[PDB]
Amino acid sequence: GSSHHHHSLSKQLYIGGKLITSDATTEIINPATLEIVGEISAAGINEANMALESAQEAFSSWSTTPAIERAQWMLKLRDAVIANEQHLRECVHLEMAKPWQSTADDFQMLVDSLNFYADAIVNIADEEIKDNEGTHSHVLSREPVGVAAAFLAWNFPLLNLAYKLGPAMAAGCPLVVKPSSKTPLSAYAVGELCEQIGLPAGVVNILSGMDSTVGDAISASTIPSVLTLIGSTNVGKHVIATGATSIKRYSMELGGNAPAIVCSDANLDNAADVICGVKFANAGQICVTPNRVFVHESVADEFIEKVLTRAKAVKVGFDKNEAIDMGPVMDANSWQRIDELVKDAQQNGAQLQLGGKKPTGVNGYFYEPTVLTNVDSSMKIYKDEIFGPVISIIIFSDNEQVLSDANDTDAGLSSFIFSSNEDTISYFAKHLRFGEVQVNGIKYSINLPHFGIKQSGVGVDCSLLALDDYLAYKRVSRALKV
Amino acid sequence: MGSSHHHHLSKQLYIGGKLITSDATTEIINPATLEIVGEISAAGINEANMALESAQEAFSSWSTTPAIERAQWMLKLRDAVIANEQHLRECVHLEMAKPWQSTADDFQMLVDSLNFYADAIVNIADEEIKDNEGTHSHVLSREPVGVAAAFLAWNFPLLNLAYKLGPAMAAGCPLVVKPSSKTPLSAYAVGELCEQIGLPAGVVNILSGMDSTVGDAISASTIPSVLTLIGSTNVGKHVIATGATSIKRYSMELGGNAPAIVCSDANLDNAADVICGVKFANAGQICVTPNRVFVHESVADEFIEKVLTRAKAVKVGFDKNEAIDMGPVMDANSWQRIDELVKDAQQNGAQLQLGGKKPTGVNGYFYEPTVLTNVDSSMKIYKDEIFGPVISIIIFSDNEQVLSDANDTDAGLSSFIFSSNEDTISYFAKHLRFGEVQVNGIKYSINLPHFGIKQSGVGVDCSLLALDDYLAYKRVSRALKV
Amino acid sequence: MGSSHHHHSLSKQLYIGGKLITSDATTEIINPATLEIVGEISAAGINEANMALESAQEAFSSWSTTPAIERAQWMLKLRDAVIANEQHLRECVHLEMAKPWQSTADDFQMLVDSLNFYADAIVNIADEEIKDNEGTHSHVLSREPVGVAAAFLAWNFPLLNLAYKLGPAMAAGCPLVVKPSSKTPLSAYAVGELCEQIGLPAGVVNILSGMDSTVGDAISASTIPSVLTLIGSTNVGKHVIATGATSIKRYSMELGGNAPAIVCSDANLDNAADVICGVKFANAGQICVTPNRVFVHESVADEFIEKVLTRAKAVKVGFDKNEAIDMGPVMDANSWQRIDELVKDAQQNGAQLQLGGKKPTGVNGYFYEPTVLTNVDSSMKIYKDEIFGPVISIIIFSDNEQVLSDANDTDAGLSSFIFSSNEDTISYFAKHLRFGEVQVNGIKYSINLPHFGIKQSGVGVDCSLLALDDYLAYKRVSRALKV
Amino acid sequence: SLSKQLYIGGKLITSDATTEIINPATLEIVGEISAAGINEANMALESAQEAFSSWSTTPAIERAQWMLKLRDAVIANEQHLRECVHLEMAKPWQSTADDFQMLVDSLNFYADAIVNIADEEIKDNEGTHSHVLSREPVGVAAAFLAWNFPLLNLAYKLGPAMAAGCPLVVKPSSKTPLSAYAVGELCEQIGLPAGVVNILSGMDSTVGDAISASTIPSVLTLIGSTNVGKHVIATGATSIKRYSMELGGNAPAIVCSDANLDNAADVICGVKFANAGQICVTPNRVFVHESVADEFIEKVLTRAKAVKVGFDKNEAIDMGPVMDANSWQRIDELVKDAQQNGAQLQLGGKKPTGVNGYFYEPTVLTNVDSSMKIYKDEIFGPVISIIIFSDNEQVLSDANDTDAGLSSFIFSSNEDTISYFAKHLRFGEVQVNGIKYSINLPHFGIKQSGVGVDCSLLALDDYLAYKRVSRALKV
């Protein structure tokens, strides 16, 4: 699976504590059935400015609301999320054809984050700093930073929202949320729940619209003190440059290219379950999933056989009342991009062992579980992020050489090492230039920090560190001799 | 101790462990005598690219050099700095016309930072993270980030270098430094000391050149992982946009507009000593020095009299073998900018109590200690950063009203409160929207965090937190069931 | 000819090094009338920009040494492909900025006219012998290709702005790197497709769009270009000059304008209203040479204002290539708000809104109604700044010598207009107006007529033979006669 | 011995600072000038701006009359003008004639050219409009002059600027400011209207940047180094300005096998030793074919031995010292770096015996190749670096292997070798079997050597702006 361990189809914008319409609508098409599943009120530049000014107007009172009272609001919203679980998961199911069991990750992370950051914020304590000369006292404290704006990717609509909504509410930062236009229903539904519980106006705002107009207007605004993004590396560079109209804190999780190293002493059944599980969950559209699977030559044939067995057993389709393991990819551009990487690999010598096409007799953006062997470092599927249900296998023999190959990327999100040797595990854990090194498994949770280095982004999601973006320091220094 | 920092010539480019010349030179003019006092080899984009490429090649060896061993290099450099104290302070004296005693801030902060961060990096310890499900173990560690680049302001040529050099060396990031072309001599002298001790090539690089070409080439390069800047908010925003060729970490200290509030129950002698001390130290060219002095009407006549007495006793001039309190400002642009702020205030009702002109019979960029009263929120001197030896006084009546006036700025660096009332102190310390609140005094040191909020920048200089920009996290998670 | 220029798309890839290529990025194109996506381009990064610069550099020795006859042959082969794809090229301009269908002809036709004019001009370039006063040497003065050229194009005339640089650069054998505005890149990307179709030699023409602070700065800061040319604002003009200082480069640019249009007591009021209204509402007033300050004499003020209001009311506003539309919307919301602030600022300082000054009722896009303001004075923002919109700003004057000082009271120096029947008055204003162009009782621009500004409006000349000067470098060969 | 004041706003004024001028041959003080500060630079710029409306509207016939009046005073003060040059940089008396004569030639050439400027009619293809193309003064001009030719460099800018009605702000090099200050005294003596010509010297970083960064100048012109040119471009970006520059060169001189070796040695040695080789168009790399190598080296050695080096107004001195200690050390390190990589020093390469002045002997280097810094960088000194070649196509590739693009030299008697090199040499000027420069011949560089043209009618282009007047014929 994803290894994220837990702890009215017409919707309007949620701006300024009210549900409002606009001058335009957006029809949402299910990527499996290609049928319209709903519509949202689409935001324009005028609606973006309304959300920003409403968030700014709320900052003074929301940031001075005691932390215990802000937590009370977070738990009241949590209780409404729990009471409306079925509709929230149905929104994600419809907008992106995510399997019904897979929608539990989105819903439950929303509950977990609300719980985690409501509990963490009431435990924040001031810190005293020693004065080496004995002349002054020093108290270090943390205060809300300002208005925050969040651009969410479509792969996990409610989980991505949970990563930002939790810390912002807890840290008293009025939040402007732009869900992806491909998956807005579930976020708009959260906005309906905020309106239902009577959340103070401006504290949370949810609006979707076109990127080059609404997205740029949020970035170029001088109101936001923090701009946070989950998306592509090129969009991250666009947000940084566009947000330069003022001084802003940036934090983003961008593209990855995770190497997975399976050694000769590795538990092959466990390595196969872990890799296939996360490579086919959400159809491989996962930031931390393996992108290049390196396998030792001595266990290559046996490991490929174990991978094919699991890949053939993946249940593909779109049916909430069946045990579907994997759905389609997001849209047509994603399908053709994945297919171009797979076909280019074959044309350069890679061997297709399974999949590599759309299931016959279907029209949605389905791509079959794919297994590619004989992949080398000169191929485009090696250099680029697949973000799809494709297992690409590279054969290695020297631990020192495969370490250099694993590091031969600008990405810096996750990485995997499967081995039974303690010196081998220690060797790769220290030298892998990645934010996360998963040993003999994979584990993510609201209390564990999730982050990338290098060109995979800035900042941390989950854990107490996620509050860093939304809290600013203050040093009060007083002379003791008055 | 007026500046509040509490302690604890033809020069070539230093690039890739070697001292090299170029095709051009830059003359350095003393701002007091208007005479040439030195020359440096000016860098072009070719020299900028050499420093970047040499720092990139050094990252593999320097980042994997043991922290104890990197600290030994920092102490070796510190030993050469101490042995060259006179020449280093002479460079600051010549390029800035700083009084001899005021060059101690530059020199001693360089020693203090090398000591503090050599000691800090060897005490960095890993952090265990608890797994709530008991299925995995989690180890959080910190590693070098990559190449760092630093753009330094001219007001503290060696102290500004100290804030970046200490953390970057300790954290194993090769550093590319661009001192201001107005004050490059003292930094170039540090490059000579680096070469003298045999520092590995690329670990430190010093080069000065045009902002439009050399500065942009450094920001636009894809090599730097961290961009740090001490400067103006316009250069800040420019660096963020031009750096958007890659994902970079940004650390900045920009404009300040510090309010200093002298209440009815304040120690007037102490308040006048602190305010006057830092307002005339370095000719008021200090990021944390008060910009707007608010004084309660009940003690305004007495406090203004104490300010004028101190301001009249300031000895202005330039001579290393004389006892001089205050030197001139940096250049003609600064002189005219300061003078326009004073004249504009006079044209709108401000009363010139002292100064407001160049002293008699001198040609350098000297500006007399200036005192203005009857200043209001509409004047340019209220809205903009003086960065000069001008005390601008506003009379207030209500503590809750003056708090709103104090916060009526986008700056977020330092602030000051002078009061003997514990409730008044707690009220201002909590509600002042600034990174630092100085109560009944002023205190800065290498162990105390120095940071600004809002449009005054992002990041922390000094204290352990200054390492955060140069260190990247890593989570190693291992399945315990194996 | 309302614009005064007298004639003689789902997904597009980058045209770099003679190949159509994709990138890791993608830029959507929004129509400013419908606010819907109409197109898609592969966005360039600094890597693609350096690929274009390097391919253009590699092509210089081969392209610059290609005979002028053969280069003009390639220019006519491109021209034939332009004519064969006129429909698609104009639909690209129509879609990217909602320009009325007839107004798209200025873009398309100037592309044809420039390819013809400079293909013919380059083959008539002859050497010039220089006399030696001492009889000791011979002197031959010739002209050669200067190097690689880079062009930054504005959005107001996507293909016409391309035409001004593509013609001369191809003819003079300078490999060209073109950066269209990211607001209107569709039309130029289509020309790149045509270049690839006819098999133009690699590196001779390169077309790419991307962010200004990254892609645009990478082109200017490159040491490869010998000539940097720009059609844009005064602020980006100064930015390009400073950023290009990494090497010695020729600069040529057309920047902001602030044209005065003086309607005297003896002017043909019908002719003056037709000319001023025609160019003020063509392309929604987004024209560098259009009047910005309309000065009208006291005795003819009321009569001229009524004639202006009659024409402004007749302007048909909308967006449909299969309807009769005079005027479309402005480019984006920033321009709309910028124009609206100028109109409201004037009202707050005493100007009288006679017509328009708002978006038309019940419409979606960035439409701004044809606007007429009277009682405008020199203190207003609308007097000091460039409107670049469909606003006629009228100032009443009484003295010809005073209105001459008022007209010259600007740092702009593009076009200017004088309407009068008095020959002495015409000679007085044409001599004393400090502008690059003085238009008397009309307005006229064409591929053979030089178009240029002075003062802070820019340097260099577009159109006419003089436009070649930026792409050609002189050479003097001097030989001692005494063997 | 002489004290010269600033010429600003039609007045001779003093300032708070002074600069002493030291002769580079005797190392003795020869005079002083009132040094300009930023305030004096603003004064000159504002006075030039103030004069623009009256001076640019002064008839071209009347402007030419002021140029000839200045010319008359220049002729009457020839001895003193050439004495300043002789004293400020120890230029030999015979060589100072080029500085003085170019000043009188430029005043004459451009006072006559401006009164013959005629409007041009442009044809309207449609017959609906008439079009007249005229030229008008651009605005205030500022000129930064190098020290190698103090008066000749001034002449290149003063003539066109006065003729085109552009008030001019002149910053002579602080190393050679005396001769130009003397011109300013003549400008004050004849009663030239205030602001039309302004002369001031000062610190490059303060006074030079204050002129470039000011928004008043419409034209920034410079004769100097390539690095200074890039600095002026970026610094002047505070407004839109016209730039015209003559920067560094690296002229290749190709001595083929069928060349007149006597004539080639005369031309090359003559210009390589005049002004101590401190000439923008002097050969920097001398390419000689193998068949004529040792015969040409011998002839070059003969003329280089006959060079009379010294500093004496009453002696027929051929060559003085170089400008300062920086230039001497820079030239010496180029020769010793070439020797350290295999260059055979044949003559000179040292300071003459017991001189102590900044003298560098006439130097001849052989066995120079493309690796050496003396091959890549501009010598700007009395050094002849010879490179042996064999094939014409290969040495043409070597000749163009530079970012410079000023002058070039081809010596050959074959008509096809002449046409082959004259076409493929990527330089602004190709001198064939000789060298010629005059006020009427255009002087310019391409590539990294600058933009714009000095001398000839094309020099007026930087100071004149076009205007198209178009009228509707049907009214």
Image (spheres, coloured by chain):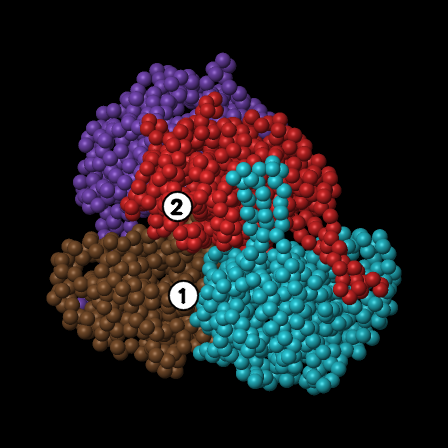
Chain colours: A cyan, B red, C brown, D purple
| Residues marked 1 and 2, same chain | no
SS type, badge 2:
strand
Q: In this view, does C19 lie above or below A82?
A: above
Query: Where residue C124 sits in the image (x, y, percent)?
Result: 37, 57
Residue at x 79%, y 73% (from the top left corner): A353
Between marks 1 and 2, how big is the CA–CA gap? 45 Å
Query: Where residue D378 sits in the image (x, y, percent)?
Result: 50, 34
Q: Is residue A250 above or below residue B29?
A: below
Residue at x 40%, y 29% (from the top left corner): B313
Which sits in the foreground, A299 or B405?
B405
- Quarter of the image where one finds residue C363: bottom left
Mark 1 belongs to which amino acid? Asn
Query: Where residue B325 sits in the image (x, y, percent)?
Result: 45, 29
- Quarter of the image where one finds residue B365: top left
10 Å crowding of disc 2: few (<14), some (14-19), many (20+)? many
Residue that extends furthest to the top in the rendered view of this protein: D354
The residue beneath circle 1 is C334
Label 2: chain? B
The residue beneath circle 2 is B296
Residue A271 appearing in the image: yes
- Quarter of the image where one finds residue A103: bottom right
Label 1: chain? C
Q: What number is the disc on residue A341?
A: none
Query: Where residue A8 sits in the image (x, y, percent)?
Result: 56, 85
10 Å crowding of disc 1: few (<14), some (14-19), many (20+)? few
Which sits in the foreground, D63 or A105?
A105
